[PDB]
Image: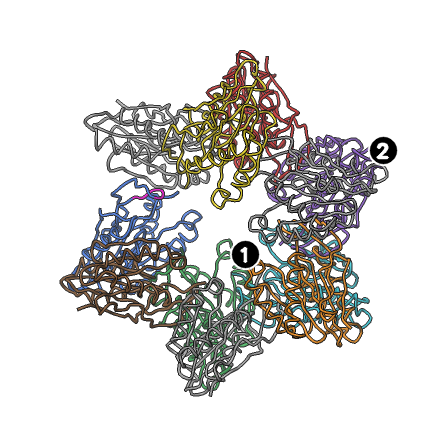
Chain colours: A cyan, B orange, D purple, E yellow, F red, I green, J brown, K blue
Amino acid sequence: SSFHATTIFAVQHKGRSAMSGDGQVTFGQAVVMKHTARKVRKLFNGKVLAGFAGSVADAFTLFEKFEAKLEEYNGNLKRAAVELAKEWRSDKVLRKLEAMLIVMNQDTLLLVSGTGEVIEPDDGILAIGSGGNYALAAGRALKKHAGESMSASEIARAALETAGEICVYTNDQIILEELE
Amino acid sequence: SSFHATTIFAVQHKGRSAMSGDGQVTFGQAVVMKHTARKVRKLFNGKVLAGFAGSVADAFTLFEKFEAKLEEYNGNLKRAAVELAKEWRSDKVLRKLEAMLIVMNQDTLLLVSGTGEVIEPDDGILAIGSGGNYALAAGRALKKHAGESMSASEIARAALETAGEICVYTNDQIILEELE
Amino acid sequence: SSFHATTIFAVQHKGRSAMSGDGQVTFGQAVVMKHTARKVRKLFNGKVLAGFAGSVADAFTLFEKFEAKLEEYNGNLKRAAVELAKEWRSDKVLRKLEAMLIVMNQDTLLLVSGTGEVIEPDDGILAIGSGGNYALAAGRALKKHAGESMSASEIARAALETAGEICVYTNDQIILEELE
Amino acid sequence: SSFHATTIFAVQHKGRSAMSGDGQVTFGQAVVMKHTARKVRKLFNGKVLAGFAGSVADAFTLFEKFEAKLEEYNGNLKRAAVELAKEWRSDKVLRKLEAMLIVMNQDTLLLVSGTGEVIEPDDGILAIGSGGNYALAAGRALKKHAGESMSASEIARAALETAGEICVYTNDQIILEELE
Amino acid sequence: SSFHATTIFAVQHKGRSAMSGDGQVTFGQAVVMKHTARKVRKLFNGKVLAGFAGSVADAFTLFEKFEAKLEEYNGNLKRAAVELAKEWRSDKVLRKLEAMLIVMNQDTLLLVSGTGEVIEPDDGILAIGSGGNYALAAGRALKKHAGESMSASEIARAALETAGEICVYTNDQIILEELE
Amino acid sequence: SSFHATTIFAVQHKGRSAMSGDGQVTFGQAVVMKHTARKVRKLFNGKVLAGFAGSVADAFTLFEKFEAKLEEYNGNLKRAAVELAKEWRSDKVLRKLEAMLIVMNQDTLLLVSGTGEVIEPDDGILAIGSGGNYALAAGRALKKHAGESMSASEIARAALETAGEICVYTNDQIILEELE
Amino acid sequence: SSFHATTIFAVQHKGRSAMSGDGQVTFGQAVVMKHTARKVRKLFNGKVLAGFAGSVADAFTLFEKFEAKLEEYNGNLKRAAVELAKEWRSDKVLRKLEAMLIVMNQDTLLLVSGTGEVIEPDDGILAIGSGGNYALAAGRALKKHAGESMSASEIARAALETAGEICVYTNDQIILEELE
Amino acid sequence: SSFHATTIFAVQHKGRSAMSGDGQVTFGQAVVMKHTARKVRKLFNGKVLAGFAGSVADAFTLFEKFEAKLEEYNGNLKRAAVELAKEWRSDKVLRKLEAMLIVMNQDTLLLVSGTGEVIEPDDGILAIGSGGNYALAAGRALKKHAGESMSASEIARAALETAGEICVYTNDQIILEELE
Amino acid sequence: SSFHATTIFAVQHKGRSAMSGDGQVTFGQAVVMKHTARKVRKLFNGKVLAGFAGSVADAFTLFEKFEAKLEEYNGNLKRAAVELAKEWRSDKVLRKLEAMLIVMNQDTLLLVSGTGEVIEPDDGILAIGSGGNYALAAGRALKKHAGESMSASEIARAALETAGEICVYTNDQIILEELE
Amino acid sequence: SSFHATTIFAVQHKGRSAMSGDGQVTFGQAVVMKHTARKVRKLFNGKVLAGFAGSVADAFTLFEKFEAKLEEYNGNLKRAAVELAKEWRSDKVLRKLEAMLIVMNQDTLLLVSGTGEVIEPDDGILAIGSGGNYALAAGRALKKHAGESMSASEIARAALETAGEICVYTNDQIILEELE
Amino acid sequence: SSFHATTIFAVQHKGRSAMSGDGQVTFGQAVVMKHTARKVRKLFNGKVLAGFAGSVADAFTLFEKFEAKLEEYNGNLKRAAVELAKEWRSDKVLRKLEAMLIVMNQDTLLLVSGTGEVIEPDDGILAIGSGGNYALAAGRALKKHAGESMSASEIARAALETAGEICVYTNDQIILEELE
């Protein structure tokens, strides 16, 4: 069989911008090889958060094509988001690729898919990978519910946390990133 | 094809005991026939909450065998929980049956399965049916997070709410039940 | 292969109560054997409308069990609806059976299923068999939009009409029934 | 799994020409990621309406090839329709592509398919994406029945409306477009 | 593998009543064991034609249950048709049974199915077994077309004839039956 | 799913040469998008009838390669028939292509297949697409049977007619073509 | 579905060398389109017999490559046999191809396969296509038993004959060929 | 989907006899409902250890039949082991059942299976449920290597420990049992 | 069928660095062809250990690309690890390839996958091929428990040992390697 | 998954009568639970050898029904062989049963199958279970080849031996039985 | 379907070097086309035995690439073995290829696989194709057992012999080769 997605969660609340992801590398059906991996990077002079879901070749790889194209247009996510899609959708080797890409900036927030989708969350919460939905369900849940009572940073941390709790493919060691 | 599960969520917080479920009846792949159904009943002189997931024949049906056996032992869920399992696990017609049964009392809380399982949630949250997990992920999420800030009743309401929001098979019209 | 469901449509608007169904008997993949069949009967001194979907054995058969139990409780659809569910859900031969049952009265309106479901449409339109949805779509659509502009009888007629238009399994010759 | 088609509906009644589509982005089995998206664009100095179904790469992408070839022949839809078919049908990457294209003009109206089909509705209603039929059913149904009673704009709106009602893959927020 | 259906064709034109069937026994995928078999019998003092499709146990077997029930009601096909369905639909061993039963009388004409269907051809042509459709397509074809120019008897003969000509599972040696 | 074949029927009787086809565009399982389409063209100074089955890109497309190669040999169907096969059989994009091509001339008559077959009907009747066989069964049926009593033109018309009558994927609006 | 192989049979007895094949063109599951086709040709100044099985493109096509390489080595079947194998086995389009090739000369006798096999029958009977074995069975059987009693020509004829008898895919009209 | 086995491990080293099992109740694909469950019981005046794997109905249920037959023969595991096999293997409801049974005594040690197997480990380690092997691997491994260095109790504990490490279906909270 | 992975195990304890793998070559379902093979090589002036899993072509092959890129950056595993990933992940022929690569150095330790993953075990044990987990289970288990009590070399040896015990795909003859 | 067959080999040479079988209990795909099991018993005052293949419930179970019926006829294997078949073939629970039964006497030798076969080896060698064929291939091999050079007893021993050597599901610890 | 492997057996005993293979060409499921074929060749001035398994195109083909590369290194099997693997593993057309290659020399002995394996039998016996295992089981069997009592040459002969005896896809006519 294959390696399982990592779970990754981005959220944007009261103008803080945040991305949490697990470390759990779940190989095969059931086996776990590692308990920690970095797939949330900081891109472009800490201006963007991007987490990928996938293999660190694929991972690294996409990332730069997002860079390249971010410079290639001086800060416009949406634009570069797109022009990557095009690039990803077309490339033989990545077009087939399963996972997605979470990109966000100071302002705004994007799902970006092997398949050439690019998605914009109405409510400032995006989420990918194994437990995705579970954390999505945590995210949206908290924001709606203890927006005032908690933070950006915090809400995301927690997303993941809940995930690992319902979710076999998600684990307690969380990486956390925010912009300034 | 078949009718989809309803989603139902029970939770027990700061000694309030609560069960929310959607109404959405999703027939076939995609079609929706109704937007309201009662599958959360009050059982045994408002002493127990029980929601089922399923068909109201099956529904009604199980319910009474839980009654019958609740009287048959003067208030002991666990006991009756079990002795139903036995009964359900064995019966030709219900043993095959898909969904589960959420039963709770003043005190405590149980999953009860066609298959003769009976389950006890460490953290006082149980959840069944379509969006289950999504609401489970809301439940556990809130409790952990705005326990103080919100209620029994409330937390459950909301579970469902979030569900319908991620979940195609779950819908906004929620039934709510609590004991005293 | 098997014979295809017939399409049947019931609706209830400004106090008239109505059931339209096609005649198309579509055998096998593609073949059509007949262009007319009656599966909408009048039941219980023209007090109820019921159409079934299925085989006229199964058809006849269910119908009487719904009779028997309608008398068995002096006009209560819902009640008898149910008690049929029970009976159908249990029976070896009818439990497995595919199609559902539309039953409505002066007052009110029910889906009733081999599976032990019994369903109540918030908005007075019910629909079964091949083109079903197509006509549910038409139903639903007419009422919201030309409630004023058209009738019970007429709205039902049309549903089917539109069905046979999109749907290869539904055909122009429609049986129409109403109560008084 | 994959993202679900969006539902799009075009219709043409008493000389107004109209395109409605939902916003529901339904990822995976059941999950919903967004509630709004634009895939109905205005093309060629607001002379044509076109909605696509698909991914905004694929979306964008097709659209321009339909531009390019619309100019390439000074207003002839049908012509360009075709010549696109050809181009789409051949291209490695778009040929396999799932969804279709609705293109209409002042005058007339076209389905255009990855497969090299190009389709002309006898009755001025075309329809794509998830709930499609549901809304085609509504479309078709409205026009036959409340042609008089309602408009272009309005009939299209409603289609979608009814869709989101039966259909779990279609949602209430509708984008509406007409030409002059 | 299994033995293939025989093809059988009944038709009723200008008040002559006629049933043709092939002899071809096609075993396994491709093999042919026999070239002649009688599955068209005369029943009830040459009052009825009945052909079955199937095994001559099953064959013989059904036949008598049609007899029995024909006497059991003094000439009413429809009635007995039905009451067989019931009987066939229910019996463990015949309910599963694939093929159908063509029954006709002086007057009228019926398909009768393992599944408890009973069918009435609007246009006085019925047809079962391998080439069914091909002969159905001959039948309906001729009647519509050289009604005047040909007979009952004749039209049926020919049905089969055409069948064997398009159809691998149908063969030239035809049995022919009519009533007086 | 996919668009269904159109049905098309060519026949050659008492030296008249004729091609009928339906209009029915059956999309998806059951849905119908259009009720009229031209896929029977006149080719080569009304010297040849050719109907295709398929997409009008594919359609148009094949057609010209038949033209081109018909000129390329001054009237010899068979020859050009073949040399197309070669061309079609080899081309990546059409070799996979499902449907076939009916070509006929003043004299004679050919099936021509994506797969590089080229076929010659002993009896001057060819037929493709959805109801094919049903009309084939009508064709061969009539000719054999009311050759004298009817025409080229006529026999073909009717083919289709019968088809739509047994066949869900075939519809009453027929296009008719003949040479002089 | 696809067209069915034609059955072809070659045999070599008391120094006569013989190839019989049917004419039955069996399209789709069950349908028959033609009753005659030539796929047994005479090659190389009536020095070789070869029948193919397949499509007359593929047919023609292979044949010439066997020509070309027969000249390419001045009468050596086996040699050219092979060198064809090579060529066929490699070619993208013919490698995948289903059927095989029977080639025989004055002297000797070969099976030659899309797969790069080349086969030599110990006992001078080779056989391909639908009924093949059936006729190989007949072949083989005749020679062992009425070698004396019958001929080359005759034994081959008969094979096919017997084929069309057991086999639905094989038919009575046989093409016969021998060398001098 | 279904609930996942719990992992249970028994081992027997330097005359102590030991059973460890996790608490993880893993429902569905990925979900976890509980983190604690007891399926290791003490049987027969703390004379036997037995853990089951399964549902606490099935669980309870088997257990007693092993009681009953343990008394039924005054301490002989193997005997009763068997006679249970027999009983389990035969019973309609338990025969199909998935999981196995670990039974051990002062002396000795048994696998016992729904299938009528009864197994004796040469080396005193037995193991069932989700992570099983993982822990059998750990078991086996510890004993061979740190027999001296560690205990009964301890070796068993650890097995599970290591399980929950590799295995997503196994979790940290371990129930531990030994006899005297 | 195919040849089975060989089992390979690397571990790193108290600064010794170790790789054990079996010799069992298990062809087909059940068959064993050889009992010894070398797929653990010493790389880069005995500075690295690497074992592959696979075919000695694939084996050899990968190995050198890991050489080449190890030189290509003067001792940095991780770096070269990656740059290999890239290369492997991309290459048509190696990308599809099943097995992974274990690479470790004086210092540190890597999984490297045809898929473009590159993995770092928190606890210094890595493991591939047939029995893998079994030995990972043993690995992991030994270190936690008899770290003190045993060595690098020894712990690795044993892993495999235990493997061949549970695992039919792993066998007693172990190749052992360490660096200095 | 399931437990794998044991391998068992019976052979009869120069009037010695012998049965060898492995011990290897291979659970699941790959896992091995035990290395020794007795499934070769001596029956009927050491007059018969019988090995079964299967579960020791099933095992024991069959055995006695062979006993019972052996007494029930005073020494006639064949007879009792048969009358067991009947018994086994019919019984609901054993008729489904996979493995077979090797029975032999002073004289002669029998395969006896769940399915109601009873088989007699021409050459005095029978063999069942995992490696069957491999040992069968050893058996027949030796006898043919070093009949003189080796024994009954010996040849069988060895069978198994070879098996475990090619065969993953067969292991070195062999049980051996002979009569006098 | 396809042609079945030939069986081929190489063995090396007391310094004689030997390769036996059957002739049986088993086509399709069950059919046999030929009873003799040479796929064991002598290569390189009778210095090497090589048998292939497969098609004589593929066959011949591989063979020379083994030659070429054998010269290309002056007698080193292993080396050339390998460098073929590389070549075979990579080539589009042979990499997919099923069977293997048995190569041996004066000294030593190799399996060589489409997949880029190259294998070395510990015990000087290799075997490929249909009955492989059966003869493998004979080979290993005899050597172990009547090494002294029989020869190289002999042992191999016999392998095959036994095969054809258990094995449907292996036949009595054996080709035998040895070096000097």
Q: What's the residue at 75%, 60% (across, down)?
A: A109
- The x and y percentages for residue J114 are 35, 57
Is residue K26 located in the magenta-colored stretch of the structure?
A: yes
Whether callout 1 and callout 2 share a subunit is answered no
Amino acid under disc 1? Ser
- The x and y percentages for residue K18 are 22, 56
Instruction: Report whether residue F178 is seen.
Output: yes
Is residue I70 located in the magenta-colored stretch of the structure?
A: no
Res B67 → quadrant: bottom right
- The x and y percentages for residue I84 are 53, 63
Quadrant the N terminus of chain K occupies: top left
Chief secondary structure of the magenta portion = loop
Quadrant the C terminus of chain K occupies: bottom left
Dot 2: chain letter: D
Q: Nearer the viewer, mark 1 or mark 2?
A: 2
Q: Is residue E144 left or right of residue K89?
A: right
**Above or below I119: residue D54:** above
Judged from the image, the secondary structure of the residue bearing numbered disc 2 is loop
Amino acid under disc 2? Glu
Instruction: Indicate which disc residue I90 carries.
Output: 1
Q: Residues within 10 Å of mark 2 (few under 14, many from 20)?
A: few
**Distance from the alpha carbon under mark 1 to that under mark 2:** 62 Å
**Above or below K65: residue E48:** above
- The x and y percentages for residue F112 are 51, 27
Of residues J115 and D51, the one nearer the viewer is: J115
User: Which portion, as a residue range, is magenta?
Assistant: K25-29
Q: Residues within 10 Å of mark 1 (few under 14, many from 20)?
A: many
Identify the residue at the far left of this view. J148
Q: Is residue E8 left or right of residue A153?
A: left
Instruction: Indicate which disc residue D148 carries.
Output: 2
Instruction: Report whether residue D60 is seen.
Output: no
